[PDB]
Image (cartoon, coloured by chain):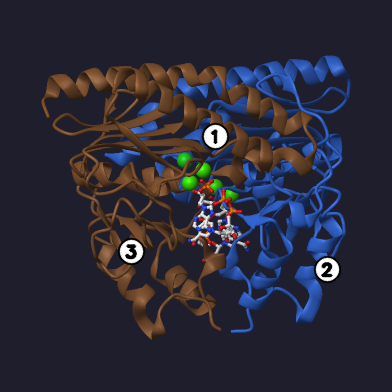
Chain colours: A blue, B brown
Amino acid sequence: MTDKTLQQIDKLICSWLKQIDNVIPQLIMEMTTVTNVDKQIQQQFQQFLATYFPEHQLLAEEKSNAMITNEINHLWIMDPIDGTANLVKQQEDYCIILAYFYEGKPMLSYVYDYPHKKLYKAIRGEGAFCNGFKMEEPPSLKLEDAIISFNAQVMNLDTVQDLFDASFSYRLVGACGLDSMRVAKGQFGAHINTNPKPWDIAAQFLFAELLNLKMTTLDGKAIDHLKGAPFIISNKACHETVLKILNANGGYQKYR
Amino acid sequence: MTDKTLQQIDKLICSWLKQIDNVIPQLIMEMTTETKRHRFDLVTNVDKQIQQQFQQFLATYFPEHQLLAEEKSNAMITNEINHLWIMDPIDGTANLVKQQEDYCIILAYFYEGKPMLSYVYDYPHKKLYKAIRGEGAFCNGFKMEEPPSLKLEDAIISFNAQVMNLDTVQDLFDASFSYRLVGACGLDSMRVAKGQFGAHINTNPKPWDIAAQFLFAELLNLKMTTLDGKAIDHLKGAPFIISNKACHETVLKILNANGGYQKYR
Ligand SMILES: NC(=O)c1ccc[n+]([C@@H]2O[C@H](COP(=O)([O-])OP(=O)(O)OC[C@H]3O[C@@H](n4cnc5c(N)ncnc54)[C@H](OP(=O)(O)O)[C@@H]3O)[C@@H](O)[C@H]2O)c1
Ligand SMILES: NC(=O)c1ccc[n+]([C@@H]2O[C@H](COP(=O)([O-])OP(=O)(O)OC[C@H]3O[C@@H](n4cnc5c(N)ncnc54)[C@H](OP(=O)(O)O)[C@@H]3O)[C@@H](O)[C@H]2O)c1
Ligand SMILES: [Ca+2]
Ligand SMILES: [Ca+2]
Ligand SMILES: [Ca+2]
Ligand SMILES: [Ca+2]
Ligand SMILES: [Cl-]
């Protein structure tokens, strides 16, 4: 793929996301008085592909994905609303996740923090950006100096306590895409999700590559972008320590 | 106090908070340029400066008005003080230092002990939550209303899990819809005020962490009490909850069951 083609696609995605701005307030007003919001955003993206990129296929949360394989050369993975609980309960702290893979290789990635008007995007060969401003590799963060984010309700409490004690503090935004972007920005040392779907993490691959983040399974391997696996996205300086804590003493799972 | 006087004071405070753009952005810049070792010290220094400047603001506009804040001695501040401001110039210090986000300014005026004006300035998002007795509560001039009823099972809750025993934390997890944490008392409180969270707990706040919230709770029909359901002394602070009216009792029940929420030993 060329830089010229990537920019053309990028230009069309940024325009689509701007059109989304024109539709979403109405969908939100209807929801208020899974949602229609998730399903409509997804359907509109499907129409966008049908119109602009007829060869491209979609793996997304609100459709069946049985026909999506590693043979598909032009693939988008979408979470149309990541943070559905935050959308419904708070109307805040949710995002749109989009990622394009070409012959299996991450080429374009998007995390749109709509409520706060911040577009994180990554373009292979160009870099990562927040609202157009180039992002750089975050400063090194040792676990003891870093805030971490994970779901404490899906782990055994002894392991949750070990994570509390070894880190600087604990926070949770509650949307995978956003908690990940805080790692990307150097605000959090690490974000963990012990059982993500492909759409929860699809954009993050390219961000992790371009910003020198560690993004691995909880066993330290590369993740299958078609399947998802227990995962971490981490600053390079606290990745090993976090994995070590999670896997010590018989591991992080609930004994329950 | 008249609506005319409150507005005059309100207008002054809003203007002063706007002028805070001359201080805060510089501290934020320095969270990048100064070494890790000095960062909390820089924040506490700028906390002290913002506080002193508010002190001077009072001396010049409101000569009898006094100030209760962290960076000054408050030994002489009593229930005898007729005109009292309580201030947290930067609430959410750890978020400022580590994230340069999710921090706020807390300011509250009490007249003869009664909450009259309150401010939570979400500075990174430029969102001024303010409350005025007789007028109501506002976010950037959009008028806030009492939130919908939220039973605990349907609500997101926010608290510091590291300061409670884990059995009680588990009971809070199981009984609520979900768990979130912003990490600044003022902001986690405003999410309760907006109906985004069912409840926020802080088991050991200072007066300045919670001073604004009294008036917001009154005007928006929120329950704001000690963890044993009493009125909180605004001069002293206590273990506290701010909650939607429909999940207040259930949360307190969970916290106080089984010997309470404290850590063991
Ligand atoms: N394994 C984990 O680390 C984890 C993380 C979150 C949630 N959950 C599970 O989700 C159920 C209810 O929601 P919650 O409050 O825990 O999460 P949530 O707060 O509703 O969502 C938190 C984040 O995790 C995603 N998510 C939703 N369901 C998930 C699942 N089953 N496994 C992993 N991630 C998921 C969300 O994606 P969408 O908003 O697009 O759904 C969002 O990005 C729970 O019973 C819990 O087991 C597990
Ligand atoms: N529920 C609680 O008792 C509670 C709540 C928060 C923090 N803490 C403890 O205090 C320390 C600071 O927390 P952090 O590193 O997450 O971030 P933080 O920015 O220091 O504290 C988070 C929030 O609680 C306030 N705070 C600071 N020290 C506190 C204390 N001892 N008790 C209650 N509230 C406090 C903060 O106000 P300022 O930014 O003005 O300090 C902010 O509103 C840790 O040891 C933490 O576990 C306890
Ligand atoms: Ca979703
Ligand atoms: Ca998701
Ligand atoms: Ca505070
Ligand atoms: Ca403070
Ligand atoms: Cl907030």
Q: Is residue A60 visible?
A: no
Ligand 1 in which quarter = bottom right
Do pointers 1 and 2 mark residues of a single chain? no
Q: Is residue B19 above or below residue B256?
A: above
> B137 or A49, which lies in front?
B137
Q: Identify the residue under disc 3.
A: B152
- Horizontal side of residue A145 vs B246, given as left or right: right
Which quadrant of the view contains residue B259? bottom left
Q: Residues within 10 Å of mark 2 (few under 14, many from 20)?
A: few
Q: Is mark 3 within 8 Å of ligand 1?
A: no
Q: Amino acid at mark 2?
A: Lys
Circle 3 sits in a helix, a strand or a loop, which is it?
helix
Quarter of the figure that contains the C terminus of chain A: bottom right
Q: Identify the residue under disc 2.
A: A244
Which is more foreground, mark 3 or mark 1? 1
Indicate the chain on which mark 1 is placed: B
Residue B46 percent coordinates (x, y): 59, 31
Which quadrant of the view contains residue A6? top right
> B168 or A130, which lies in front?
B168
> A50 or A219, which lies in front?
A219
Do pointers 3 and 1 mark residues of a single chain? yes
Indicate the chain on which mark 2 is placed: A
Q: Identify the residue under disc 1.
A: B48
The single residue placed furthest to the front in the displayed view is B76
- Horizontal side of residue A145 vs B2, given as left or right: right
